[PDB]
Image (tube, rainbow, N blue to C red):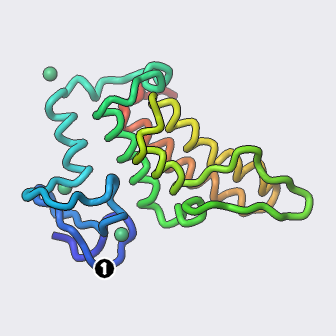
Amino acid sequence: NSNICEVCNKWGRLFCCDTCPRSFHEHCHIPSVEANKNPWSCIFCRIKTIQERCPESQSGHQESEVLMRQMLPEEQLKCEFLLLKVYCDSKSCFFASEPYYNREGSQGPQKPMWLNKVKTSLNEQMYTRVEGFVQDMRLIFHNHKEFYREDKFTRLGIQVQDIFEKNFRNIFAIQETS
Ligand SMILES: [Zn+2]
Ligand SMILES: [Zn+2]
Ligand SMILES: [Zn+2]
């Protein structure tokens, strides 16, 4: 197994996957690494199994159909993975914890949003459909763009949103288009 966490790329107290060489800090993995369970399979392994059990799940989908899906176990897992993929980028640090807004010439967003809040929401089963999760994720970056206006710091929102959107299209097998 790897000697660094797959998400944050640091060493420390790591839990190793039994079916692939990835390792995780307890609260870097999503969901948090489970108490017992030997063997234990990580979220990358669990997602791969879904695809392997239903190869047709990789055919193209319309985003509008994906968003209306109810958050049954497999969609819940897919959203957890997609959130994890965003935390894997080091630029996620900017969006992880609760933000605050005091900048000359800007007003804060009406509905602040951040990754740790989406993480809690997922953990507490607060989303009933994929759309709930996706809307909160996209709101993070939209609030950032709106607040930072012409500051070049706006680009961090663009960059992390691109990571999100690529991974959304991959995980939920959205039909490729130009
Ligand atoms: Zn970690
Ligand atoms: Zn694994
Ligand atoms: Zn089948």
Write the residue at 47% across / 35% down: 127
Q: Quadrant of ligand 3?
A: top left
- Residue 64: x, y in percent? 50, 21
Write the residue at 40% across / 41% down: 79
Residue 76, image quadrant: top left
- Residue 11: x, y in percent? 30, 79
Q: Judging from the image, what secondary structure is the residue with disc 1 in?
A: loop
Residue 12, above or below 96: below
Residue 1, image quadrant: bottom left
Write the residue at 42% across / 45% down: 124
- Residue 158: x, y in percent? 63, 51
Three-letter residue code for mark 1: Trp
Residue 125, image quadrant: top left
Compare residues 117 and 16 and report the one nearer the observer.
117
Q: Which residue is mark 1?
A: 11
- Residue found at the far bottom of this picture: 12
Residue 89, above or below 76: below
- Residue 92: x, y in percent? 53, 61
- Residue found at the far left of this picture: 38
Q: Is residue 27 left or right of residue 52?
A: right
